Amino acid sequence: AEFVPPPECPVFEPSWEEFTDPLSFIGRIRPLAEKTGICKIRPPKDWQPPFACEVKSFRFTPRVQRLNELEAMTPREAFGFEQAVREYTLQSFGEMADNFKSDYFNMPVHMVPTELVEKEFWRLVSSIEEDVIVEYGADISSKDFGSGFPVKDGRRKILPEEEEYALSGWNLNNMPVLEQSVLKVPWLYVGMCFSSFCWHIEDHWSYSINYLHWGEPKTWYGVPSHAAEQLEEVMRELAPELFESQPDLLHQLVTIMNPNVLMEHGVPVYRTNQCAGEFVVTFPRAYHSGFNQGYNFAEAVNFCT
Ligand SMILES: Cc1[nH]c2c(C#N)cnn2c(=O)c1C(C)C
Ligand SMILES: [Mn+2]
């Protein structure tokens, strides 16, 4: 009855030579990675961009997430009122997040095995006897708060040691984002234990790339694009009737589904733990979902080839 972890997605460890151009590298690994939907890329050991967000002034109001909101829908008094959220700094959010996780598991946050957090996450999502509520930061533009990468924009100070990172093609501010036609900037994610995102693809079936600047790992699940329609059919068969008819862009706001359910219906699913300093790439029309193991900070952008 415990969750069965999907097989691991490919992890690549490029040489310095392979690491010069991200689009060339992604094009070369595509024959394998597009068959798994997601892959993980570990930069060379010495590639360590400094964290460039203005942490002192970094303030944000997280949103609240109830893990079992869908299963709970199987009329509670005064529904719609979450209590409420307050404004945090990055530091005070992290204090809240660590206290939550260490209290939840009764152990220091870094001693909780990633497989236990995963098993407990999926138990909680389906449990009606236990309502767990977490908070996270998303819908956070790097244009308002600053990028996690140094940028030669004249707004902060680049040190000489930072300049190579401001100019690197793996700096997500330097990824190509313009689609060709006859006719964006990176976003930031502040996670805590159990905060999660449900199954979705990107607009225009775009690639996406995500960098975990620091913190505890981010656990991902990915489905290759060749199984996109099978995943959509399982969702339709098993989603609530009230939401079955909804357009994809709205339905993707509530498409939470245990990976084992998809696997039981023949949908291939792969997993990974993205750790600090690692990239995850999602391929075009590769459904993905995931959750955070603890307090962390990621940056992501949709790019075009
Ligand atoms: C909403 C959301 N989406 C994503 C993606 C994607 N795609 C990757 N990480 N990630 C997140 O951590 C969050 C929240 C929980 C902080
Ligand atoms: Mn995504």
Image: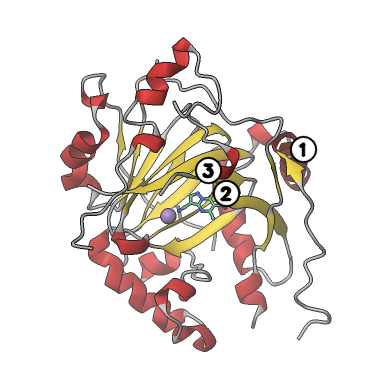
Q: For mark 3, what is the residue?
A: 143
**Residue 112 versus residue 238 in the image, above or below:** above
Residue 162: horizontal and vertical position, in percent? 46, 17
- Of 143 and 107, the residue lying toward us: 143
Q: For mark 2, what is the residue?
A: 140
**Residue 16 versus residue 42 in the image, above or below:** above
Residue 24: horizontal and vertical position, in percent? 19, 35
Identify the image's colour scheme: rainbow, by chain, secondary structure or one colour: secondary structure
**Label 2 close to label 3 by CB (< 8 Å):** no
Q: Is residue 169 left or right of residue 47?
A: left
User: Mark 2: which amino acid?
Assistant: Ile
Instruction: Bin the neighbour count of mark 3 within 10 Å (Cα to Cα): few under 14, some 14-19, many 20 and up.
Output: few
Residue 141: horizontal and vertical position, in percent? 54, 47
User: Mark 1: which amino acid?
Assistant: Ser
Q: Which mark is residue 92?
A: 1
- Of 35 and 129, the residue lying toward us: 35
Residue drawn where x is 58% and y is 43% of the image = 144
Residue furthest out toward the top: 160
